[PDB]
Image 1 (cartoon, rainbow, N blue to C red):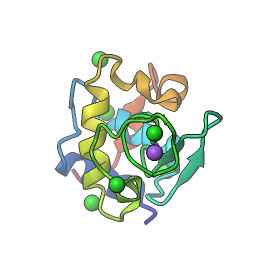
Image 2: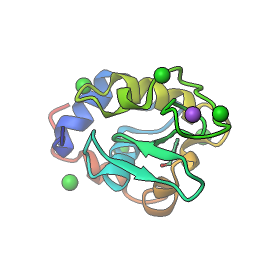
Image 3: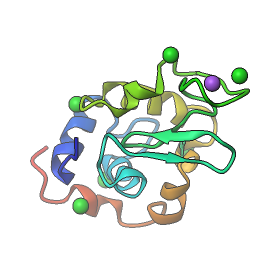
Image 4: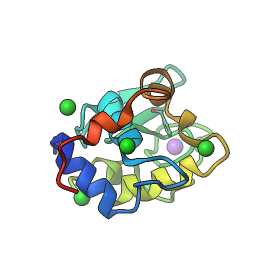
Length: 129
Ligand SMILES: OCc1ccccc1
Ligand SMILES: [Cl-]
Ligand SMILES: [Cl-]
Ligand SMILES: [Cl-]
Ligand SMILES: [Cl-]
Ligand SMILES: [Cl-]
Ligand SMILES: [Cl-]
Ligand code: NA
């Protein structure tokens, strides 16, 4: 599923990400834009052989099981395919665990490079929330 900008903001807010660990909704929407272009089915292979899955490009190196990432963990206790569903519940619950792990949203390199310190509120502007 490819979400609309305000549609995703709404879904993210409903699932508890607005101001989760102090990150306003705009941060999460900005992150999703540059990670996946709002596409739940996005997948991208990493140099180390791991793969990133879904709207927030969650990595199989630590967070989910895809059966093909040697020496990895599955800390969210989910198959990576669950991260590609039109329903973002699994992605959100997993992102909550990740953002809580010590480094905040810096875990998402695209957030650090493209969203961090920017006017992220613009990503939720005009949205019925
Ligand atoms: O796209 C980077 C990333 C992968 C896995 C968890 C958080 C961030
Ligand atoms: Cl957009
Ligand atoms: Cl915001
Ligand atoms: Cl293994
Ligand atoms: Cl599994
Ligand atoms: Cl949803
Ligand atoms: Cl933080
Ligand atoms: Na594996």
